[PDB]
Length: 48
Image 1 (tube, helix red, strand yellow):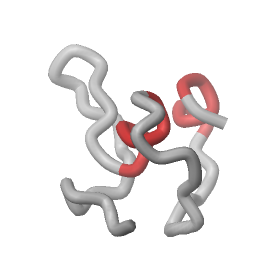
Image 2: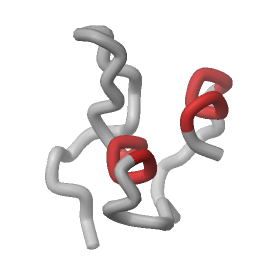
Image 3: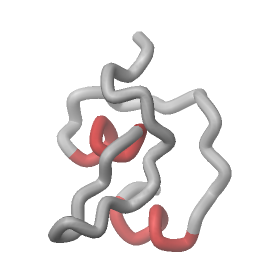
């Protein structure tokens, strides 16, 4: 399944949001991301 928001994770500074891949990996709406997923240190805090 392609993600619906069409974004690469990439922290959303509105209040702390996570508009991309990692939104699917917080909300348990998708449990894998074999995708462009260069490990970012701030992503390590909220996903693994």
